[PDB]
Amino acid sequence: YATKIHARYVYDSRGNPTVEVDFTTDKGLFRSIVPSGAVHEALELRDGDKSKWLGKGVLKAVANVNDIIAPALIKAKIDVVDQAKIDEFLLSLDGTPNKSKLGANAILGVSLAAANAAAAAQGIPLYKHIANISNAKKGKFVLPVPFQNVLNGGSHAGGALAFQEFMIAPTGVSTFSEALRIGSEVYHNLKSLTKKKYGQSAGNVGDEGGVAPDIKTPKEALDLIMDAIDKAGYKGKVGIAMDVASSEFYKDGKYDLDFKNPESDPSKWLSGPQLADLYEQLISEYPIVSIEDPFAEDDWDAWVHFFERVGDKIQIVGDDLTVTNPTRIKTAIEKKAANALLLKVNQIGTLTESIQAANDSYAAGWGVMVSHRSGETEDTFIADLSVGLRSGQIKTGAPARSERLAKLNQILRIEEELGSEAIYAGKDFQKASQL
Amino acid sequence: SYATKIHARYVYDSRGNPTVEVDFTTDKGLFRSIVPSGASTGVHEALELRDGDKSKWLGKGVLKAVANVNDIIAPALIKAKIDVVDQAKIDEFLLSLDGTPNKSKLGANAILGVSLAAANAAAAAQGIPLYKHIANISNAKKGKFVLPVPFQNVLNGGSHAGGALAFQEFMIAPTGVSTFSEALRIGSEVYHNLKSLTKKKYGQSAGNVGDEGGVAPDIKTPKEALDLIMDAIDKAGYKGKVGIAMDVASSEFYKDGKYDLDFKNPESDPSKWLSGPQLADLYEQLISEYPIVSIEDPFAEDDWDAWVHFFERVGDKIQIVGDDLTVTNPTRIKTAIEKKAANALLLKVNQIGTLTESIQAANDSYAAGWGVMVSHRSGETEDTFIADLSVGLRSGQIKTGAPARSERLAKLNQILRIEEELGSEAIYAGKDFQKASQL
């Protein structure tokens, strides 16, 4: 099926090189771009030549595709519709467990481009191919709740605020079109309120499109967002999600909510139980629907205890905890540490393994939030992935840079194409695969 | 081949506001174009039609323009069965449907999407890349294709970024290398060095970006921004190989016949507002102090006397680019040519609204010995048309953002693909950017 496979480098949304693959069949040319990657994830290959792109070149990974993968896969004459055989072959070219000989970024571009070639071979949209090969439940397609970054903290902002991301989730409407419109309106009201309260510069955006004013406390951030939802006119219709990224402030088995302060008073660092009390207070006060990485990546007991406290009424999402890694995912399921997975395809390195991880999550009753990376591209693959996997949830940025909006625009085209055969996940996003 | 189906929808641009996207189907398949949108439009631009319904998208919906495509333009054009390779006949038909000089009946943002999609369908019908079709219909000189110098807006100010900085865009222009690929690599390395230097001098928040991907420090003088960029070039290792360009967008602070360099300060004192002559003297100092190769909109969009005076002083030393002055409009370019007000056109297809009129604007400029810089808007999309346009027109110059947000990199990535496709058949404009159409 594959008659020509060619890779090149292009630039990602932060100005760093990444791998793009042209995958040619008799049905035409199909292109994928790998987002930015990285002990638990598959390893992206960077060149390390400090004199070019500050060591971030990907000419070696590009060459691994053109010089090793392309002639091997072409010679194998594998039907691109058989995604599992394509990926099984890809993995046979690299014997390391983390794809470190060829590069996760070299392997993944080929995996994804073949999926695009296969959809066209069958005359179906990519999300329908993905629904087929992941064995999604038949019925109406489910369009995802966009979990939209609006406000950034932690490592991404000055001021004391320790939590890394605050997102809006427009769940209280009946269509994805309305959800995205309300999301854009709330985001614009938040930018306006941010500039007035924190100054004009505070309205300049970070890597994922959100703002990063100098905020002190979680309550201040959450109040700001609540103010934007109300001023935009959608009080009661917009949930809030947090990505705490608490590994960044885990110290001596406690949690330093002033970790950016070099004088941080250690007598105020919170135990596991005290941080759970704090989250439970915030849950009592705000329409928080999902919390990502509330406890540190290896603080397993803290996750399990917290999940028994709040797990039946809020989504708890592993990111640093699970790293789209089968062994870690199986651990978290068996421990009952969480009930939802961030799915980063370039953390695992092939589409088949990604679909496996998503299906193992669904089988445990977990949710799946298909996720962007900080270094994104104009590629829209994860939009079709979230629809095809029936995840009902996607995390792909603020509504404010086109490597973010390109995914959301693609779901707009999917929604229009499907018409009455699609359903917006709305408040049912946690269990959307079962709708 | 001719259109079999034409369908429009709204999508979201890089600022989160709706814009128009057109699906143009022929026997060769479906061709998609997306209309960009400026955050600060010149008063003479063709009309961008917005709905003004304040209960939806804060009045910035484009449902009317989308319905104008679906309900007026699409059935009429499909009926006419116009050969898509005949771009002028396509655009003449579109223009007849609207019948107004500024496209205010249907909206330039309903017309342009169809115009651009037609040209993509035309390239497919002929089995050639878009940039080659554009070279053909623009009657570009035959020979090597010319790849453009990427003018990268690495420090944002004015209406594109919160903070005190009056001038809208400070760009680097990596002219002192031999290939487009090297120019892009150097551009990214200078940008990353600039971001590091900016955060260490102005704080972490100053590394956040404006609309076009440039860093946005809260600085007050052009000298501060230019020193920062010079330091970034030097520390990256490319001293002497990178020119600087500015887009002043001076119409944004032209008030009472003077120029307010503190215009985002609501308490800006009118005593410090500069006259035309005072502003020209500041440019002359900056041109001497820094390797500035191009200045865009140095004076306001109808302040003809000041443009003429400034051109007399430095028109032989630097490129002087009309943007709001000319709005990619042949009638205003004629005035600028005859008055000797500038020597380059900023080509923004959506300021005039059809490809054919945009190409006429470029060819009128070339005929006067002017340069042409093909340009994005600050509200951009994943669309990559202007990459091929800059190559096809042989402009040697493109302005499509900093190497940061992907509505900017998408265009530069597309030029990387064109470069690789062309191989020895392409030349990098390099230091010859100003007269690249004659190379």
Image (spheres, coloured by chain):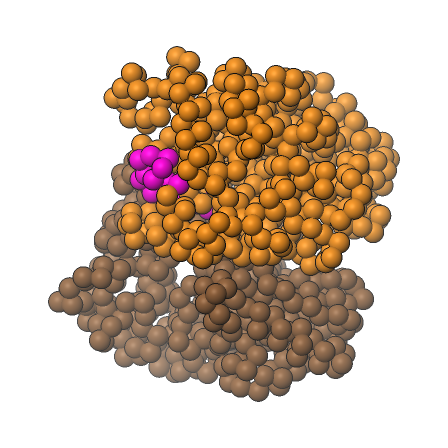
Chain colours: A orange, B brown
Q: Which residues are magenta?
A: A208-222
Instruction: Choose top left, top right, bottom left or bottom right for residue A188.
Output: bottom left
Q: Farthest residue in the left direction? A: B271
Q: Which residue is painted at 44% across and 29% down in the image? A: A279
Q: Is residue A152 left or right of residue B49?
A: left
- Residue B46 x %, y %: 49, 77
Q: Which residue is painted at 51% across and 81% down in the image? A: B104
Q: Which residue is painted at 71% across and 73% down in the image? A: B85
Q: Verify whether residue A102 appears in magenta.
A: no
Instruction: Choose top left, top right, bottom left or bottom right for residue B385.
Output: bottom right
Judge whether A70 appears above or below A419 on screen: above
- Residue B437 x %, y %: 53, 66
Q: Nearer the viewer, residue B12 or A71?
A: B12
Q: Which residue is painted at 31% across and 32% down in the image? A: A160
Judge whether B44 appears above or below B61 on screen: below
Can residue A194 be seen at all in this image of the molecule? Answer: yes
Q: Verify whether residue A216 appears in magenta.
A: yes
Judge whether A365 appears above or below A396 on screen: above
Q: Nearer the viewer, residue B169 or A375?
A: A375
Q: Secondary structure of the magenta portion, mostly?
A: loop
- Residue A107 x %, y %: 69, 31
Q: Is residue B348 left or right of residue A9?
A: left
- Residue A322 x %, y %: 59, 24
Can residue A67 be seen at all in this image of the molecule? Answer: no
Quadrant (top left, top right, bottom left, bottom right) of the N terminus of chain B: bottom right
